[PDB]
Length: 408
Image (tube, rainbow, N blue to C red; front, side, top):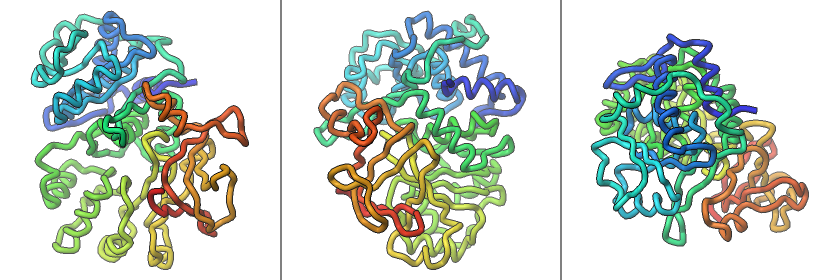
């Protein structure tokens, strides 16, 4: 029975002086991140934030962003990422759809929401007020079935829709991920993606709930591979989490040039696209098996990943096949099925639709009951449970690895 911030709080208890977050603009230890998140959370509580309250977060990547996420969680609310690089109309739509009455933002993003009548907290300008609130951990603000965040994803119907993720599926993912990646207190993880993508949660919580150090990327280091590698080297990053497309760029430029990977880097996690077997062969030819390379798969509706494959552990023959596997379930309470049109399990190598079941599942879509009933289906073979219909085709290989066959 645990929320994501309770996991974080236990870590803070273990290692209060360890560095939690580092950016170009400063750093916070575990104790400092916790106390500041607590101050903001107490404030939020006075603004009426409580379990099930949706709070928008429009912030750039920064120490402030991490404090704000944790503070919203601790207050018992669920955060809705609002990417300040998005146009006004889209952000305003998201704020109206989610009926957000509290917005955590910064002065520079002021005017980004159209005639917003709710409460605004600017983290950069208001910190003196916030420093007047209590630094102590809040208690019992949430249950595991309460929402942690609602993250918007593209609608085919022309508007995006909020995917509602509860603490329990997030905590489950985070614990499975920490064990799978072997994150320890000596790891240094680069935070790469915008929080508008659920992968950022991976980067953030896995890092902070393990006692590792979270390093926030800059805007400049992404612009060229050489700069990305050099900056990573300087920061002694041990874990990269990369969109597959950026990883493709990385392999291309590795081959084109003499660049060596940071000596500190032990793990590269990729996902989000079909991975090119040729680029993988290239990677294994030039890089070898260190750092480890892991391909991760899952929809936002499955709490950020349900399956992984360790690419560095594949035999040459498994690499020379026509598709790089998306592998096996992240854990036992997460089920990844290939099913027929009757929702029946199928024999190996038989193609079918991928459906996800068990603890990974989102609550559903926010304010889209038709789409939710369409996508999240009661399991006829397990009445008390649901399956999420991915729209992904796949098949399980004889060796047990799942293979992605594309979109249905």
